[PDB]
Length: 326
Ligand SMILES: CC(=O)SCCNC(=O)CCNC(=O)[C@@H](O)C(C)(C)COP(=O)(O)OP(=O)(O)OC[C@H]1O[C@@H](n2cnc3c(N)ncnc32)[C@H](O)[C@@H]1OP(=O)(O)O
Ligand SMILES: Nc1ncnc2c1ncn2[C@@H]1O[C@@H]2COP(=O)(O)O[C@H]2[C@H]1O
Image (cartoon, rainbow, N blue to C red):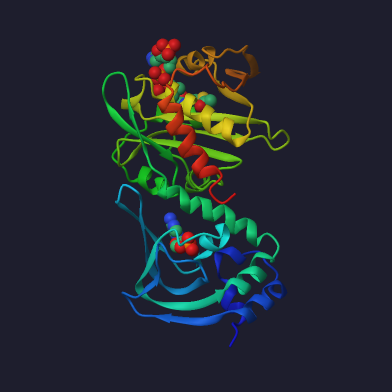
């Protein structure tokens, strides 16, 4: 009954893989056909199953404890059902066919053989937590002047959210951040967007719909105990204390991630960033003309202006995203 290796060769998780690598698995799966409106999976059910989508589309619906449902979509080239099999846990979501759908599917054993394809298990994990991040609970954040926002992790869709959003990021902003006043290339947006949360962590703050700002760190290639950090705040939200908060938040996430030292780079002439830094120290060095750097140990307990309940919620959400699949 098995699948033609070509049949699986389009699936995102298999890209780069040598055809021979896929044969055992291609032998371990059966074809699946489903009509529009049909239910493939359900949120509490134990996981016996996984599916790879050749054609059609499916709605993903997750009911949080609040009782409100986050929705996403599963599309051709994508696995679904992998996560519960990854964590050995219940279905994270209910999955329903939108478009009539095909149709490669397998069981626990096929999954095993799949995981044993080199660098496949890793992709699966990455993408898994990537998806689980949508189900985490956005933390209410009320700044000193009363304006109310939300703290959550970046989602790939933030990319879209931001490009077509009504929130303005000035050329001067773009320049202070990326050193060009121009709007970020699609390639770049993808980079800022899709992350593993392990070597690349990103906070976004929103008005409750659209992201108004972000803070991220990327673990150093050679030294995993240090990461370079960066921030962006939308023009009209600047100067209200968002950046200070975000370095706190980022610091909690960092602590979780096993990161110790933050590295920073910036225009010598960008005062607020420098000020934020200066609160923790530390000495500035000149990296290049008009450009400065620095290195700080990560505060750390007692060194944060955030709160207790607050650092609790943050550390909780962060750790929830980071260790979700491991
Ligand atoms: C490592 C990197 O990310 S470098 C580049 C950073 N990103 C950018 O430059 C992009 C566009 N500009 C921004 O995003 C900036 O507004 C940020 C994020 C650097 C600043 O953070 P914000 O959220 O805007 O304001 P925030 O309230 O956190 O400012 C922090 C500190 O600088 C002070 N500050 C605010 N505005 C100004 C200003 N116009 N001039 C001087 N100091 C200022 C604040 O008082 C505060 O100091 P304090 O807490 O000791 O009193
Ligand atoms: N945000 C998302 N985007 C795409 N697919 C998802 C998302 N969240 C959950 N899923 C899939 O929905 C499945 C529901 O049950 P599982 O946890 O077995 O595995 C889950 C994932 O394969």
